[PDB]
Image (cartoon, coloured by chain):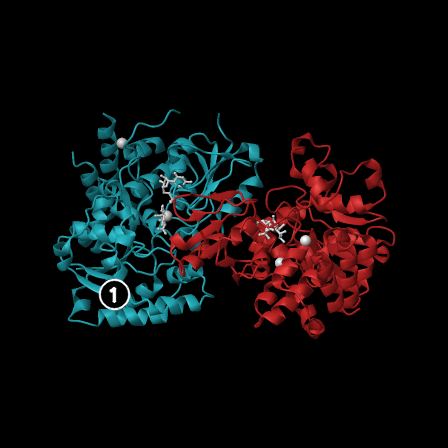
Chain colours: A cyan, B red
Amino acid sequence: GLAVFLPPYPFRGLKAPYLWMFYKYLHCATDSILFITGEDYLSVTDDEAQRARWEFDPASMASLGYELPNAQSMACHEYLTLDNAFYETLLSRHHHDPIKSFSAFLTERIPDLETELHALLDSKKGIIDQIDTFISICNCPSLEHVARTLGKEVMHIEIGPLRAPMYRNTAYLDFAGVNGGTEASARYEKCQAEFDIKASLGDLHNYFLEVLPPAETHSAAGVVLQVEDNSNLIAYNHDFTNISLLSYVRQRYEKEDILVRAHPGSLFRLRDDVFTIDDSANSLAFINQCNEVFTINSSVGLEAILTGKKTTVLGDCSYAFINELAGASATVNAAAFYLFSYLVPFDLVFNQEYLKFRLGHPEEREIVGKHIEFYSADHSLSSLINEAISLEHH
Amino acid sequence: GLAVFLPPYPFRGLKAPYLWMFYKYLHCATDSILFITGEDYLSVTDDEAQRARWEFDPASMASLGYELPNAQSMACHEYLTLDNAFYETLLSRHHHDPIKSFSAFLTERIPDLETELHALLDSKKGIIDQIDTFISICNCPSLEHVARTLGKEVMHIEIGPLRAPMYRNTAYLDFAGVNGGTEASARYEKCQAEFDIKASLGDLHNYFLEVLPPAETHSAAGVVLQVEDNSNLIAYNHDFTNISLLSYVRQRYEKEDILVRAHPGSLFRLRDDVFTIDDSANSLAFINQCNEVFTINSSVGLEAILTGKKTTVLGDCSYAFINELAGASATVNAAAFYLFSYLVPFDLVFNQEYLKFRLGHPEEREIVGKHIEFYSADHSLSSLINEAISLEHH
Ligand SMILES: Nc1ccn([C@@H]2O[C@H](COP(=O)(O)O)[C@@H](O)[C@H]2O)c(=O)n1
Ligand SMILES: Nc1ccn([C@@H]2O[C@H](COP(=O)(O)O)[C@@H](O)[C@H]2O)c(=O)n1
Ligand code: NA
Ligand code: NA
Ligand code: NA
Ligand code: NA
């Protein structure tokens, strides 16, 4: 079955950092799953000191589509637990900087981590033989090195750039890496000639919109800020930060022409003294007020591209290649492939039958057909997409 | 005379970034000064688009002790102007990141910058021969390399860690570097045996206090945040940031025991959702509520040390060596030397007669005597300091 890697290391000061994906896989589980995680994941619940975490909020559970697991739900899976001694040692090897330690976890092999993973996997039965694929919610060269030795693939899976309530929920599934080192551009290059999409970028954007767009005083430049310690601002940012992104824009625009939107999930908000601060209810209403958008690698950059805004992308990300194409035609085709073939309907990356489907490395046409079938729960590759858009049209 | 280096490069998006020091040297000038700067410094005034800058606020002028220069005041100095073409080229050589470019300016030689400096200095008269010393408000290996070739010293000068209205105004003057690569520890090591201070750390703190201390619900841990793009968070931080500093503390304390104070000058403030946020009127009232303090390299770390608080200093800074001494005795002696001999009364670093004094590299006893004479505008080195403290006592 699946071997789901959810490391317990509190790089950003939060225990069980990926608890929500632990609950989601448990909720959707149809067969037994091997969880490679930490005891923090198994004890967080019956810890009255953490009962206020957002993962326990009924609104968050309903939005992500999971329910809290019970004793029975968990008893049907196998659990391997990583110890904290390695984490303490890791911090001591990077000058006690937890963020730099996180960066090494995301971008370098850690031999001591590989040793413990091998030991855990070799600790029982034919655990290794039962493994059809690894799943990791982030890049992890330690795990990926172990996977090569054992002949297993690594699916990198995470929530996608389009999310409810504004959009249909999407997710990433990438065999090379998630956010950084992605294979979206490589997949597109191989089937680019198979795309003749009779729709505009706005039509593709409209297909994923679940709401009526906001009410269409422009700012010349909009600046998207991100969560300061998110993995793709730590590892895939090309050294840019929120503050150097702001300086970058101020080299090109006077502060009176800049509109800044802080990430609603950041610990930091902006003072009103310097820039004009955005107070929009959503990121779409914000970029609509801007003539061009600047981002490191926020999901919002995709929104700007799909709405036809001049967009600068300074960091590595899965959608950047769409922005690097000359000519409207190729850009629409690249966006269509990205949205219907690279992105996955959110629930499907937690579906074991779908994961087995992707493990066979099927053709892009079959992948698109699976996604549209799901989106359309109510022929060439372009025919599938053109007809899907057209049926949504009327 | 003096050759004052005030570069015009808007690394942080602000033109004439050190305009206030330009006005201060002009205001206190008794002789002709050579200014190596940019045209932005000379035109900012009669630019109605910048008349709201804080350097023009009468309260800021009175606090820093300068008045706006007029046509006559400036006509008695010589001006060399750096061009912007180099800045544009510099940005293109660091992936258009202005903050990374700033870092290179602070920490690396830039041959093209050295060439332009040499050309400017060689552009007229015996400009070079009239130069008694360079003054730089930041570390600049480009300028320091030029200085070596020409046989000139470089005084690194900046506002100090103790400032009005809470304290007597102080400044740095350091021949090796300011903030980073400082010589405070080296100077202390040479005369440590000459210090037998009959006062406590609180007594030294009281000497520089100009106000009555605040009214003495403790938090186990206080976190000092800094301005995100200040030079000593860009170049001398050992890679730490505000966000990794927070994670560092969260590895040791639960959020309920952490009190966070954002820098009043930062563009960012903190949300109320996670940590307990400090709303003190000053940094002293904040650290008084904490049992131990954490900082990268804020001036506030010195305050914590002088008030006897357990202090963690993660970045490079001039006062760190005080915190690395074992035993209360040596710590008080180190603090006394730092405060009376390393730190300079603010006005004196703009006084040409005092600068000439320091250019002779006098003995630590003479330096302390000059500073106490200034502080006391109303004998061994320890006798000078002990008597100064005692006279302030009664
Ligand atoms: N500056 C920002 C960044 C993100 N966001 C919201 O957060 C979601 C994910 O964004 P990141 O990839 O930037 O975390 C986006 O779809 C958008 O809904 C926002 O509203 N403003
Ligand atoms: N978190 C912080 C940082 C600085 N400060 C104020 O700013 C002045 C200089 O601090 P930095 O060296 O941190 O810029 C300090 O003396 C203190 O008065 C504050 O009040 N809170
Ligand atoms: Na991405
Ligand atoms: Na739609
Ligand atoms: Na310092
Ligand atoms: Na005093």
Tell me where residue A346 appears, x and y as whole percent. Answer: 25, 44
Q: Position of residue A179 (x, y in %)?
A: 36, 51
- The image quadrant of residue B376 is bottom right
Query: Which of the chains bears the disc numbered 1?
Result: A
Nearest to the observer: residue A71 or residue B109: A71
| Extreme residue in the front direction | B394
Q: Residue at x 67, y 55 (%)?
A: B208
Residue A200 position, x and y percent, is: 34, 31
Quarter in which the C terminus of chain A is drawn? top left
Q: Residue at x 82, y 49 (%)?
A: B33
Q: Is residue B99 left or right of residue A317?
A: right
Q: For mark 1, what is the residue? A: A81
Rendered residue at 41%/61% (across/down): B252
User: Which residue is depicted at the point 70% across and 73% down?
Assistant: B190
Callout 1 crowding tier (Cα within 10 Å): few <14, some 14–19, many ≥20 = some
Spot the residue most to the bottom. Answer: B193
Q: In the image, what residue type sits under mark 1?
A: Thr
Question: Is B205 located above or below residue B25 in the figure?
Answer: below
Does residue B122 appear in this view?
no
Is B354 in front, or is A3? B354
Left or right of B315? Residue A27 is left
Horizontally, is B18 left or right of A335 in the view?
right
